[PDB]
Amino acid sequence: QALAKSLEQMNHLHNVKYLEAKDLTDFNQKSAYYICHQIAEKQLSKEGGHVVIGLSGGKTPIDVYKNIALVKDIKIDTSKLIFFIIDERYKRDDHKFSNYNNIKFLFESLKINEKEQLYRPDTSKNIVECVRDYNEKIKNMVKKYTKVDIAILGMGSDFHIASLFPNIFFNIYMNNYQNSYIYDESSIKVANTSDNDNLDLLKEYVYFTTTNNFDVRKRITVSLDLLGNASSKIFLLNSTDKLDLWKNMLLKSYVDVNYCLYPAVYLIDSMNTTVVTCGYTNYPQMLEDIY
Amino acid sequence: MDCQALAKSLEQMNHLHNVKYLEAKDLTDFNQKSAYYICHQIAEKQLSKEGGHVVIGLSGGKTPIDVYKNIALVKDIKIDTSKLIFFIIDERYKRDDHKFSNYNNIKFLFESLKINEKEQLYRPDTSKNIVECVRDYNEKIKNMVKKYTKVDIAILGMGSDFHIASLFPNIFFNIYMNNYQNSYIYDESSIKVANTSDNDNLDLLKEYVYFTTTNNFDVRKRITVSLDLLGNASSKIFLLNSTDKLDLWKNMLLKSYVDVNYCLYPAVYLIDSMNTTVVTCGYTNYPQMLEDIYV
Ligand SMILES: [Cl-]
Ligand SMILES: [K+]
Ligand SMILES: [K+]
């Protein structure tokens, strides 16, 4: 009620909607409210009611998910929801701190039947089989339910989203296609053609990617293409540091954006990206000043 | 500039986990101390080096440039500038316009020192196409190393993505895809890639100079000397003159404590290769802030 006013105070700038929070509590409430409003709007217009929602892990999304339970004035049929894990930190031998295990309280809160309503990687398999298996599962999800309706995302200090780590083309190619380790290399002809056009060649739904060992080296991620085709992308940027990064991204991507380096901009350019913000008052004015 | 106080500075450097830290009081002291240290390193190495031919690699950017401006000011020790050998550690490549290049931004140093660039400076010919630019500079650097044995001093910074020179994480993926894939620059068959560790694959890279890429705002196409070349330098000097840069170095050391990937944290390769020094500004008793990583 206090929150439904505020979805109306929303700023639009260069095809992004910005929703501003006043502090971290407001952020988590406003974010959870906006996500429920999107799910309900989508469900109301989808024949069969089966809204497909991609979830990221991490502290910022988790503290938002904790508030989803609290949302009471929005009618949603939770038995028809379909969830999938956008990306996972792979550790075959211990799953304790995984994104799934850190966010699964949400499924319990909403009384979700995970066997029927949740797609996630089987991280008990070896990395190659885990990736190929989750690929086919996401493929089947998209066939059955047409597309992703809502993707909930964050962004790291290296501009990565999901586990799509710059340079997304090099990282995907070297981890999946080189030596046909995961997918057939004969399928793809790299030119030495923009990175953007090269990433176009990679047609799978799920890939193996890598980052540093401290952050969990081996990752499973849905593809940038899958996320760009989502009907709604929601970024959760709840600090000045994150808002500073988003601004600098927009500055540096203004000319000849390489989507392999700034994947969030691919989502922007694909339309229907919303950013919820906390840290700066009148943040969208700060951005207009660079334009 | 007070060379008397500066000399004691150098005697007072702190050591932690095989790195030397030289702490500046403020930004002006950072520039003066860094230039003083580099000069003294050059002069001492010239007394031990074959024919006095100290080999110095130079980075560009504001931070090194402001240090280079102070190299003139250092009067308290003899350097035979006619014997020095310089090279460019990395370059931002634009075939059609060179005015914002590292070379062109730092060449005032060569004029100041009255350097004969034809005889004493190795740098890329960025009027060449990228493939030939890289192969030409690779051969120049190879010739430099054959003739002068190895790099004596490498002057470096580090970026917010942990890159140094133009060695952009993931260094193996970036170098492979830009140089070896489809034999664009070097032969694909000259290297057998495994899906082992990134460190082991990095070890397979044997050239001195590579093509790398980053974002278009920062100039997409880059020429860089190899991580191996830098690791073999007798002295590596990092110039970290802000708390942002010092926060990055500390985060790096935290995250690289276990199973460091040198393709993602190249500076740690340099640390592990020994003789790395860091000059710092922004945090008082900075090594104290790092201590507990190791104890
Ligand atoms: Cl990469
Ligand atoms: K898991
Ligand atoms: K140049």
Image: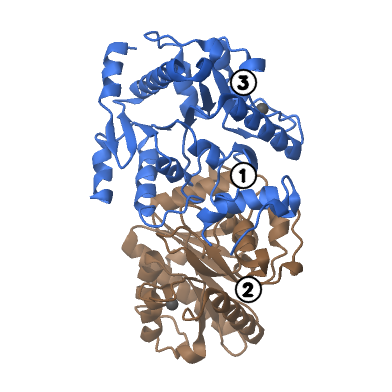
Chain colours: A brown, B blue
Picture disc at residue B121? 3
Callouts 2 and 3 close, C-beta under 8 Å: no
The Cα–Cα distance between marks 1 and 3, rounded to whole angstroms, is 23 Å
Q: Nearer the viewer, residue B106 or B4?
A: B4
Report the chain holding disc 2: A
Picture disc at residue A105? none
The N terminus of chain B lies in quadrant: top left
Let me know if residue A153 appears in the view.
no
Query: Quick one: label 1, few (<14), some, or many (20+) residues within 10 Å?
Result: few
Report the chain holding disc 3: B
B236 lies left or right of B195: left
The Cα–Cα distance between marks 2 and 1, rounded to whole angstroms, is 35 Å
Q: Which residue occupies 47% across, 29% down?
A: B155
Measured along the vertical axis of the image, is residue A139 above or below residue B260?
A: below
User: Does ligand 2 reach within 8 Å of label 2's beta carbon?
Assistant: no
Q: Which residue occupies 41% across, 21% down?
A: B41
Q: What amino acid does circle 1 point to?
A: Lys
Q: Nearer the viewer, residue B135 or B65?
A: B135
Q: What amino acid does circle 2 point to?
A: Tyr
Report the chain holding disc 1: B
- Comparing labels 2 and 1, the label whose residue is closer to the camera: 1
Q: What amino acid does circle 3 point to?
A: Leu
Picture disc at residue A205? 2
- Comparing labels 1 and 3, the label whose residue is closer to the camera: 1
- Please tell me whether mark 3 sits on a helix, a strand or a loop: strand
Query: Quick one: label 2, few (<14), some, or many (20+) residues within 10 Å?
Result: many
Q: Nearer the viewer, residue A243 or B24?
A: B24
- Please tell me whether mark 2 sits on a helix, a strand or a loop: loop
Image coordinates of residue A38 in percent, x first then y, are: 51, 74
> To which residue does mark 1 refer?
B206
Callouts 2 and 1 close, C-beta under 8 Å: no
